[PDB]
Image 1 (spheres, helix red, strand yellow):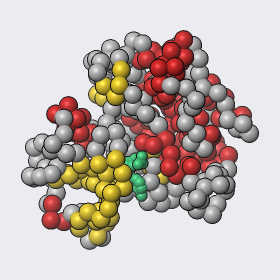
Image 2: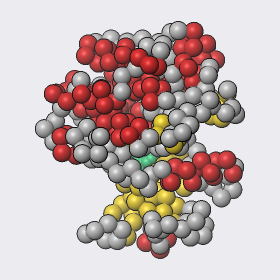
Image 3: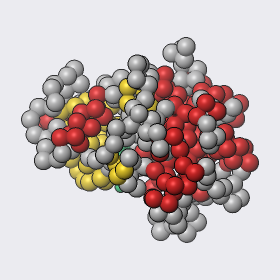
Image 4: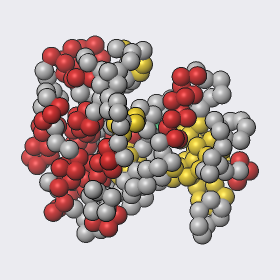
Length: 300
Length: 6
Ligand SMILES: Cc1cccc(Nc2nc(Nc3ccc(CC(=O)O)cc3)ncc2C(N)=O)c1
């Protein structure tokens, strides 16, 4: 625990409903009161964990807030304040009007019971997402961090349909180390991790890069389940053996080309997120340059 | 889809 500069008074917080259960916490939608410059009512997302939950988990939580206190990037959901005072601990953050990317993607299938009345994303639209997602993962490795769990569900859509990286439960610090040779005994997303980490537990920039191609696969397949039909033990053997995911039908060719570059069996061959943004800067939204990171001065 | 393992 331990109160910070981010500390917030619990009284200002009111919880409305349950948005969902994530990698390990609980996410409620609520309204903060006078927390930002201007408005007195700024509905937010509140992630919490049970003070009746495993110490390992509880710690995983402390860590998530910790690494969010930095992270000032357009394409990263903003941490908004903590509430360590008493019970229970409450981490607040900017609510993303359109939920996770996964859920949002599915809601666009022509079929869809919850379809918002618009067509599945145009090719223009996909590039944009891919870019802000990548931009954000770049900002990450920049501040020296591996995300270890990049996937549609952990990407939130803002109101302007902008995409930002969310959920940093597996994110790790990397001067020195610049790994984990893993550790053992823990929940892992096999469908999204690179082959090395699947055997030689590790996780690196090139690793998240692998996870990144799967998000594109997710985007294109409209949130079909990666490696559907297979069991987690089967996929485990497969991607380790030397296999890779397929390719959605009617899938554009520019993207497919990206996916491939993310799937070399050798990590030293995966492009860098920055290198990915570059390949896409000439086809983005005229606004991207200003809120960007690829253009941010910090990109040293 | 976070299967335990090593
Ligand atoms: C409107 C809406 C609807 C659903 C989720 C969110 N927002 C958020 N959701 C999560 N985790 C989160 C991610 C995926 C799920 C979907 C599922 O149930 O599997 C639930 C919660 N984390 C941060 C935010 C946020 N800060 O906006 C917002």
